[PDB]
């Protein structure tokens, strides 16, 4: 998880 999905979509 290169941030993608986590740093995006979550927040």
Image: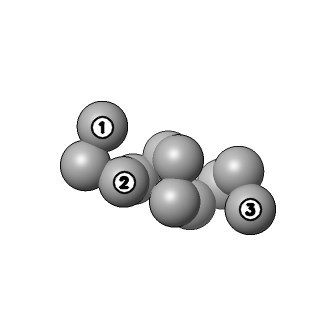
Cα separation between marks 2 and 1: 5 Å
Q: Is residue 8 above or below residue 10?
A: below
Residue beneath the point at 66% across and 54% down: 9
Task: State the residue lying farthest toward the right.
Answer: 11
Which percent across, then down, holds residue 5?
50, 46
Query: For residue 11, which numbered disc appears in the image?
Result: 3
Disc 2 is placed on an element classified as loop
Residue beneath the point at 51% across and 60% down: 7
Which percent across, then down, holds residue 6?
53, 47
Residue beneath the point at 39% across and 53% down: 4
Q: In this view, does 1 lie above or below 8?
A: above
- Reading the image, the residue beneath label 2 is 3
Cα separation between marks 2 and 3: 12 Å
Badge 2: residue crowd in 10 Å (few <14, some 14–19, many ≥20): few
Question: Is label 2 in contact with label 1 (beta carbons under 8 Å)?
Answer: yes
Query: For residue 9, which numbered disc appears in the image?
Result: none
Q: Earlier in the sequence, mark 2 or mark 3?
A: 2
Q: Quadrant of residue 3?
A: bottom left
Question: Is label 2 in contact with label 3 (beta carbons under 8 Å)?
Answer: no
Disc 1 is placed on an element classified as loop
**Can you say which quadrant of the picture contains the C terminus?**
bottom right
Left or right of 9 in this view: 5: left
Cα separation between marks 3 and 1: 15 Å
Badge 1: residue crowd in 10 Å (few <14, some 14–19, many ≥20): few
- Reading the image, the residue beneath label 1 is 1
Disc 3 is placed on an element classified as loop
Q: Is residue 11 above or below residue 6?
A: below
């Amino acid at each position: 998880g290169s941030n993608k999905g986590a740093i995006i979509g979550l927040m």
